[PDB]
Image (cartoon, rainbow, N blue to C red; front, side):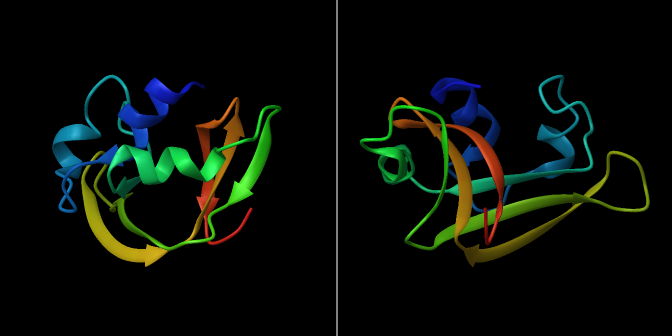
Length: 104
């Protein structure tokens, strides 16, 4: 819902996200899945440069993605690493929402 919350929810400084640890916290509250982007903040914020009004944008470059997907056991996850483009909601030159992987 802003740049600061987007970073906390979707940016990681490690590709091997500890899903069972982080997803069990109050911010994620054991949700079914969450996608983390393994990258420095600048390359991610740059996706939205020049865009003022809310608009969904698909990245032109590929990024390292770390997905935490829930297993058959509640709040227990499997980490899936991949490289793909993603869709984000840009508002006032910064990503504020994560839409999805591969397409908008």
